[PDB]
Length: 90
Ligand SMILES: [Zn+2]
Ligand SMILES: [Zn+2]
Ligand SMILES: [Zn+2]
Ligand SMILES: [Zn+2]
Image (tube, rainbow, N blue to C red):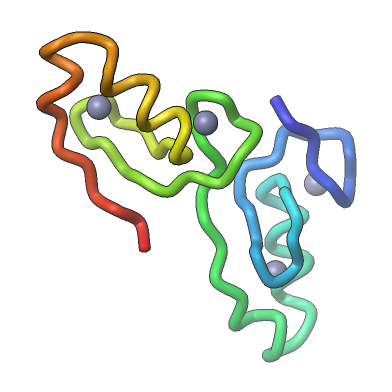
């Protein structure tokens, strides 16, 4: 798994575009509790397939938030995966 950019001792779980940062859950809380300005940052779950990119699609059938590339790889695999309905997370 991609490491947290601040603590570099835990797997990242969220991605913050404004900070351009992959963060584990505790570092995410510490960074955005710092003040009201930071607390407005919108964050997204890190892809649960590759765990190295921000997720862009939620697939409830797979119970997985996936980045664009993992979403395409997983759902082109075969005709059952191809019918999965995903929710754009934007
Ligand atoms: Zn961390
Ligand atoms: Zn942020
Ligand atoms: Zn991915
Ligand atoms: Zn799926």
